[PDB]
Length: 585
Ligand SMILES: CC#C[C@H]1CN(S(=O)(=O)c2ccc(N)nc2)CCN1c1ccc(C(O)(C(F)(F)F)C(F)(F)F)cc1
Ligand SMILES: O=P(O)(O)OC[C@@H](O)[C@@H](O)[C@H](O)[C@@H](O)CO
Image (cartoon, rainbow, N blue to C red; front, top):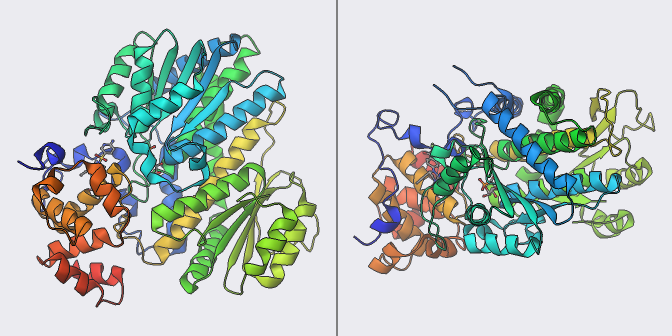
């Protein structure tokens, strides 16, 4: 029938009480699951939220139980990390014609960029030619932009890959898709498998391959699941690899910028760093070298969340500035500045937030005076300003900007990293009375830029800002249980996530949910057969431009009413959240 080709794969809504027994829940990919720790996230206070997310993050390092899914510390996964470290090594022995590409969409794409810089530094630091590069869905502009729509073309992914792999002779392509989901990556991996003489694909993500995405891609014949299954068959001959530990669901359902982005770093930094540090000792990489690094990353979580109360307070200040109608500026230096930009930008799509609401800044890339001349004027009593630096940064540039900002703001706080027994110049550096000082043990590093210290600090800052930005919005009532209902449908995955939320919250059939959704999207046009049959991109392109699509669809369904009736009901409610929550009641 019209639409059956498109919606066939969608599992029917189970009957009340049978969600587990239908086998429905066993088929939700881990990355889209509701984290049971965060059932009541929308009720947690700020200190709870910090605990609940610290806990969710901790699951990255939890070990496999005794019938179960492989995790990061499982032997299958470390063995795969080892073999890949090895394959990277061959390339490092033969830089001529060699390349190593790190590729993802969205936050995977961001993560790729960072890491390609770090390992390019490291090779430059040694005066070797840089061998790394990155690819992001939608080109380089995508690194610091909210561009959720660009991940849906496999041909695009391949094109980018063709550009960068020039007339290289040996290319390692690390495709990063947390949900094993992005069409952008699926095409790169598939292309690699067709030219093994040159390419070596390594796929990274956090679902078992049996939960890899399996709906059709518009410009491609195979599905992610098929590609990933074929790569696993090739692994037995070491010509592809799949690195896919379970890290448990995100604290905000399907918010893979969080754990998914973190685990990507942990996993890839570890492996590549092992590869470099063990070539120049003419020793193979071993699980023991990897483990040293992983455990260090695991400490860094402990270190990071021991500052939980200060993190909860900063969350409260960010939430107030937004509760009023102010803005939040994240001011940081080198790499941690970039991370700050990445966080803020991600709030646009992740929470429907305007780009001013939580904005990032590197010293988007505004120099010292430039920030003071341009952005200093725009500040206000209600705003918040977060400063993010190490003690190694150039603190004369820092004190200035804070001195000045102090006057116009007062809600400032800071995030400062430091090797133990560095001191904070100005004993009056209060300024920040109750700083978030993150003091790092002395670790033994041989490489020149002390890369493990960089990685430590990056990740720790990422954890802090993610927990803050995310928590500040939950506090404003904008999340439902542990789901962001009122998202903007800007790609196919998000279209599927919406439909799932309509089934979950209404309990009504897949045909009703699909119909209500397509009516909400295309209103004031009725449902023709063409529309029912249209490719998911047609729906996305049109929903992408509208507001409250999902909440309208749900109300239509709950009130068993038309889109005309549901809209009018919304506009007659105090707020979207009250409309929905009380309709659900
Ligand atoms: C319809 C549907 C659905 C599934 C899968 N889709 S998907 O884009 O096709 C996809 C994405 C990644 C992947 N590995 N496999 C499939 C993404 C969203 N999905 C999903 C999300 C959330 C849910 C939930 O039921 C819950 F509770 F499990 F999270 C809901 F709706 F409540 F969020 C269920 C399914
Ligand atoms: O890496 P994935 O699963 O392919 O997801 C890729 C992107 O959709 C994802 O990173 C998204 O941009 C983030 O906003 C999710 O919080």
